[PDB]
Amino acid sequence: SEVVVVAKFDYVAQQEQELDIKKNERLWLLDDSKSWWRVRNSMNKTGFVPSNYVER
Amino acid sequence: SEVVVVAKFDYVAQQEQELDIKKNERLWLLDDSKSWWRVRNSMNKTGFVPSNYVERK
Image (cartoon, rainbow over the protein chains, first blue to last red):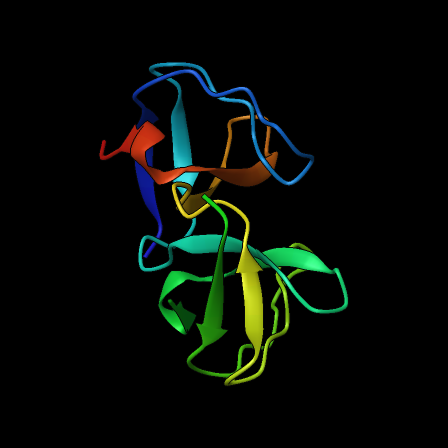
């Protein structure tokens, strides 16, 4: 579900896929049912997948 | 911390920033301390931020 969220802290993005935000900024959370991990595969391609799709 | 994870399910990436994976594939989880939400700002730029950095409004 799409909901509005508020930044608790500043965040300086470390990669182009990330977003710079400031404390108290309001953002659209596009899908509150989705959390993501950044993973890298055996072919050295990197990207995001849903957290519940992988496990230790 | 970096750990190796196993895909529980196939996943077809929906955007260029996501990764296609197959069930039972082993992957590097680059930092298991980071769990990300995809958000969009007032300037209509979209990207990932760590989930503990935002909450409902």
